[PDB]
Length: 140
Length: 141
Length: 140
Length: 141
Image (cartoon, rainbow over all chains, first blue to last red; front, side, top):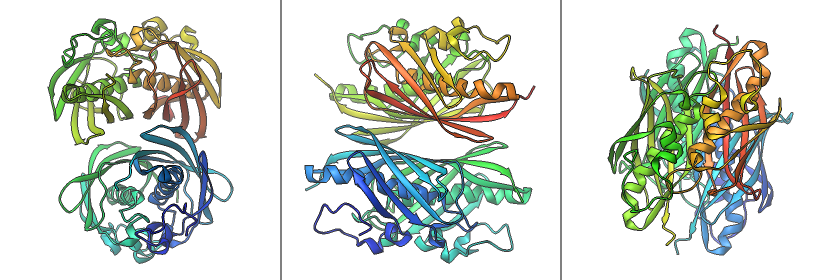
């Protein structure tokens, strides 16, 4: 269910109705140190000029990094929420796919940080996101 | 225009309703060379699976608004505008209502325009901000 | 003593030996919501090309925002430390002064955020720093 | 060169020992077009009043290293390099020893080069990172 980490028995929003399921984001690999996700390009991922929307690289990096953090911390009583997403854009994508790889570079008790790379179908680095994720005790 | 994006051309490659912006419901309200506003009604399409507005939705509203606010001025000078950096910081979740964005221009150079975007909930509280850096270049065709 | 907020009876490093005192940073106004600081340009503030070093705008914003946070939270048992400093540069400065104004835009229990503006002697916006400051209970 | 910055000119406006870099003691070790290293011995000149390395010192080491690493390649092509965005994130304080920086080039475009800089303490631990975006432009003289 986008293959998001299954950590709870109920989720307030079903994959298919969330922003992630509407645009088509899917997790491929997840480990505590490294995760990957990808998306086919369709108009839903696009802005009116025909290119993948800036916000789409933002949202992908945000979901991958956060949920890669939930994967470890949820069962320890904690919740994870993005505190900063800094996305920089090097090359546009008109069509094909966007592939993200998140590499964990810091795992602290109140903040985890992930370096995310967003690549096109030729493997070219099209964007990066520095993802900073607040970790806090879950509200009952 | 669809979403009331600025209309600076006679045709666009992708129609509003089919874009990410028109799928999640972003709408521009005011638009001047130094300040622009936009809003969006929260529905599940804007949320992540835990029931709150998706961090990426704030990113994307700020991106569209700061980008197109630049487009509204530079297109007719034969420039294009493409986001070069979006740095969004998150202070408070939104579960429902609206997200309202205001983009304030702080720097208008020949190659980069910079907009500070604030993202507020229905009670006026600052839930997120985004520093939008927009590259301005000549239309390559 | 750079006019930094006087909140403790002892400081591990005297103003004059710190980076701040070496380059000349001085606080003018401080309130919980807003603070200002400035610096004369000298070679110490410069890189080899003759212009104020990028890192100088970074360090100014970092000290102003952090210490404007210490001013309120120290006496409540808390300590403040920068968690992110994002500085963007719009115009160089060769000489004169750099003036910073920090505007608090969020004051949460674990993070305060400040918008800092770095201006030249003509008032022109030369850089900005988004300063994110972690607030944590002080280690005894 | 002073600080072992790249020597790409016969004269510089400000001598190494008088600059911020030479005042706090920054030194470049390796320098290639895709990767550069630099380090600095912690002394009080690097610290803030609470006894730890000043957040701005990390900012400044990353700024110099990513900037000059770009200079080393573009100067002789008649370009200049100036930092456009420095985004430093702080994970662990350093009280003493060294700070060691490695800058890894991740994007080399015609108008922007991007370097990921990591800042490590004497035990190898990642204390800070900086995303360095460098504008590349023609020397305006």
